[PDB]
Every structure is written in structure tokens, then in C-alpha cells.
Length: 392
Ligand SMILES: C[C@H](CCC(=O)O)[C@H]1CC[C@H]2[C@@H]3CC[C@@H]4C[C@H](O)CC[C@]4(C)[C@H]3C[C@H](O)[C@]12C
Image 1 (cartoon, rainbow, N blue to C red):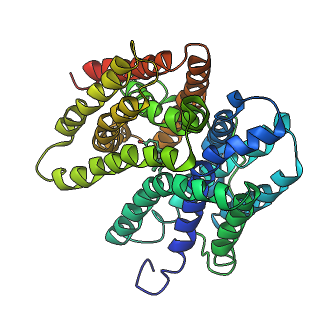
Image 2 (image 1 turned 90 degrees about the vertical axis):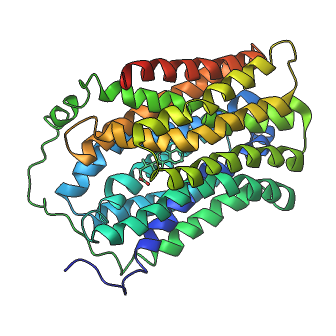
Image 3 (image 1 turned 45 degrees about the vertical axis):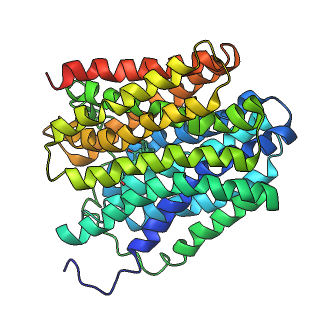
């Protein structure tokens, strides 16, 4: 009725779509420089790829979850994977940057599907301990894809063009898609229910008014932004800005990332020894020194990219520790539905990220490299403020 040990070929179809989606950001960003030095506009449009790719996610975010309830889980999930493979290749026929966004944004809306419909079909079919192994894997995906995507994204620009990636994914999404064609047993018990959408944001306005949740979502939104600012701009920061090569550049991704995960290995090993509340304040020191250090560094010295990247590691480590923990408490900051609390915190996080990245954009151009790190501190500051309230 629920689980066994034989239909494990289906979750890997979901986990593979999860994989191919993140790298859709975590490889293209370095290679966007080649996409920028071809479409003709400027290096300012490098990060602005990630941005439109994000802003898509939070679009149907809130709708697809209840929508996948009203009209099945199988067809909603399929329409998404199709939509992805479709847009993964139809992008190679745009050939201009004012409408490079358009399709980048369309692949962006193909992100809610993984959580809104996909993740639910595991909290509906498979049992507790069965799901636990599945999710801790899904956890690793969203950390390895950004960790090891940029390395393959740095070789792939040296050994191939940028067009090679867009196919490779539509392939990797169809790899699991033809694995999902006849192996996706839906679990939606709301078929034959009204198209109630004009009063759907009512179940949303309840969490949207929670003086504790909102703060805790923004505590989360901001705290992590600096990470994705780098992820968005490190191509330019380094290859152009600092004047470096794809080895000396792709070198700098890992120390950040390797420390990030060092924050997860220890988190998993001290979730036992220590309480949740403690862990966030326990991770709220390395960060606070990271975004201290990153900027304290680019004060008089404007080009010391080593110690900035070294800042974003102290920075990086603590994020492993904090974020995750704080996620728990932001969910249970509201005594409501998992899905809607989730729908909110995500439809917030991105606003923070999408916009966050744009404000981080000009910050670099105009201000140089200094301002950038200060508009990193801000959010350290920002986050920390939210904490002085949150726990006490
Ligand atoms: C919204 C899903 C929920 C599905 C799941 O539980 O796996 C979660 C799970 C993994 C999460 C991502 C992990 C990688 C990133 C870690 C950063 O420190 C914060 C932003 C990112 C980009 C996270 C954003 C978001 O919070 C995700 C995508």
C-alpha cells in the first residue's frame, strides 16, 4: 500500500531532475562569459542570467502545489519535465540577449515542479524512514550540483562550446523522463474539486502575517544571499574582473564550497550533541567573521581576491551549520501546513535572491570590489539583526 524495496527506480527519476535543474545554473554561469562575448551587450548581463532563471521559480511556485492536488501528481510533474526539455533546446534558436532572458526565465519556472509536485509524491507514497533516506540524498544533490557543476562548467568551455550543455541536460531530464513515462504512480486525492484560486491566497495570508515566520524567512533569505551573489558574479569577478583563467578561477569555487559542506558534515555530527537554537548561534560566528573578513579585507586593498574568497569560506562553513537548522524553525514557526509554509518561504527567499543579486550587480560595477563585500556585510548585518529578535 505504501513502500517496499523494488520500485526504487522511480525516486532516482525525481532525484535526476533535481540534479539537472541546479547545474542548469551551476555550470552556465562561468560559461555565460562566452554567451556574453557572442550576444553583444555587456558583462553586466553575465549574472543577470541566474537572476531570470531564479525569478521564474517563484512564479507558479504557490500555484503548482495546490494545483498538483486538484488535477493529479503524474500529469503535473510530466508537464514540467517536458517543459524543461522543450526550453532546454529552444533556447539555442533565440540568438539575442534581450530574449535570452525570456527562455532562461522559462527554464526558471521549471523549478517549482521539483518541490510543489515532485517532493509531495514522496510525502504521499513512501513511508517515514523510507522517505528519510530519499531526502538526505536530495539534500546532497542540491549541494553537490553547485559544488561540482562549476568544475565541469570550466572544462566544458575549454573542450567544447556553451551550446553543448543545453542539450546534455534536455538529455539528462529525458534520461529520467523516459524513466518516468511508464513509472510514475500518482497520489493526488483532490481530483474533482473546484477551481478555487480566487480564495487560495487566504491560506497564504495566514503565514504571510506571522511576525515570527516572515522574519525567520528573511533571516534565511538574506543570510544565504552573499553565497549566491558570488555564484552569480564569480565568472566576472574573477575571469574578467580579477583577470584569471578557468583553472585559477574554478580553483576558488571549491575552497568556498568544500567549507560549505564541512558545515554540513559537522551539522550532521552535532545535531545529536547540541540543540537547534544553539547550532544557529554556533554557526552565526564563522559567517559573522566571514562577511567581516571578506569586506574588512577589500578596504584599502581592492584586489586581494584570495582573502575575499578566503572570507567567503569562514562565510561558507557557517552557512552549512546555520541555514539548515534555521530551516526547521522557520517551518515550525507556523503551526500550519508544510506545503504552504514551504510555498511562502520559497516565494520569499527568491525575491531576496533575485532582487538581492541585482542590487549586488551594480554594487560591483560602480563601487568596484569593495562595495560588493559591504553589500555582502549588510546581509550578515541584516540576518543577525533578525536573529537578535528571532531567538530572544
Ligand atoms: C526548496 C527546497 C526544498 C526541497 C528539499 O527539501 O530538498 C530546498 C532544498 C535544498 C535547498 C537549496 C540547497 C542549496 C542552496 C543552499 C543555500 O545555503 C541556500 C540556497 C540553496 C539554493 C537552497 C534553496 C532551497 O531552500 C532548496 C532548493
